[PDB]
Image (cartoon, coloured by chain):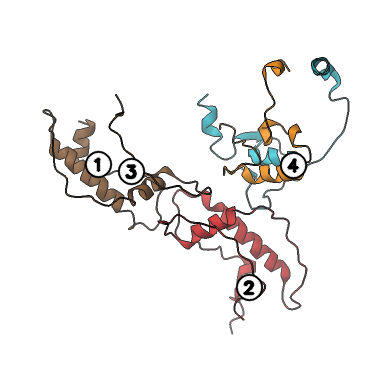
Chain colours: A brown, B red, C orange, D cyan
Amino acid sequence: SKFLLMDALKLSIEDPSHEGEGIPLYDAIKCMRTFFGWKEPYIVKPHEKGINPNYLLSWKQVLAELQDIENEEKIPRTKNMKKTSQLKWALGEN
Amino acid sequence: SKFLLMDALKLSIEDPSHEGEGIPLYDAIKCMRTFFGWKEPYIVKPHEKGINPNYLLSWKQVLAELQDIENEEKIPRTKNMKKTSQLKWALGENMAP
Amino acid sequence: YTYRCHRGDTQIQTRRSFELKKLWEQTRSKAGLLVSDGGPNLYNIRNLHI
Amino acid sequence: SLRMKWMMAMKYPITADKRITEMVPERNEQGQTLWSKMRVMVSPLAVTWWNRNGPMTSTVHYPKVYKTYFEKVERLK
């Protein structure tokens, strides 16, 4: 399937006010800020095909790029990732 | 006094999310959105020194510039007003000896 | 959803909300307002041909 | 239709004649724009504004040939 069914859990936002209409990116950021307990990631079940360090680096890059928005003076509406080696391999650009 | 005391009212955003810590500009915009009832402004007590149409134009410009945020690719953190004739007169930028 | 025309007594915020509110608070018989501008829906099985 | 739900999300998707300028103001009370210059492109807020406070004409020759529909309404009640 495209998305998993039984195994999903959610990070809720705890009852937004009735006047809250916004962009999905900032809703996602607000949902992410409500969680504590992140640690150093590691692989627990390999894929038997492909390169797994690329997956780990992709997840780390997502975290860093989401945390690296405060350096911009004109905060944007959509986020464009940077074209890196692991991401190019994952998306099959070559 | 700098700000009037007994004759002031408030436009409340009421409750913000307990985790909401944001820029004052967007708090002000959200407070503004919860009000309906604007009309066409007009003067009921002149200043008897100065030009009152400049005051009317300043209020209209503030309202329009606050509404015109959506014509921007990126959302700004602070708002800088245009240097207009009435604002220049109000701030006294052309009475410098 | 597609034409941004919700009812006058609703909390949904769009770009058309202000004028819909102004029209809603101005009218007296609110059942004669079209759906395209902040009105209720009176269609049922007996009315489908009108 | 996905085409219709792609141009209602952008400003000025409707066309009208130049006489709109002399009748509808450029901005409303809150400060929202209603039309733009380079026929001219207008916004649905212009339609709502006209329905709110615009010129009123009470001619009866407009529903002239519409009286066949009212018979159904009269028969339904």
Q: Amino acid at mark 4?
A: Arg
Q: Chain of mark 4?
A: D
Residue A80's label in the rendered image is 3
Residue D36 seen in the current view: no
Please tell me which residue is depicted at 67% across the width and 28% down the height of the picture. C41
Q: Is residue A91 left or right of residue B95?
A: left
Residue D25's label in the rendered image is none
Marks 2 and 1 belong to one chain: no
* 2 or 3: mark nearer the eye: 3
Task: Residue A51 in the image: state x and y as whole percent.
Answer: 13, 34
Alpha-carbon distance for marks 1 and 3? 9 Å
Check whether the beta carbons of the residues at disc 2 and disc 3 lie within 8 A of each other.
no
SS for callout 1: loop
Please tell me which residue is depicted at 17% across the width and 45% down the height of the picture. A41
Task: Residue B38 in the image: state x and y as whole percent.
Answer: 69, 55
* 3 or 4: mark nearer the eye: 4
Check whether the beta carbons of the residues at disc 1 and disc 3 lie within 8 A of each other.
no
* 1 or 4: mark nearer the eye: 4
**Is B16 rendered above or below residue A77?**
below
Camera-side residue: D69 or B41?
D69
Check whether the beta carbons of the residues at disc 1 and disc 4 lie within 8 A of each other.
no
Marks 2 and 3 belong to one chain: no
Identify the residue under disc 1: A83
Residue D52's label in the rendered image is 4
Q: Is residue B42 left or right of residue A81?
A: right
Q: Is residue A66 left or right of residue B13?
A: left
Image quarter of the C terminus of chain D:
top right
SS for callout 4: helix
**Is D72 rendered above or below residue A32?**
above
Identify the residue under disc 2: B90
SS for callout 2: helix
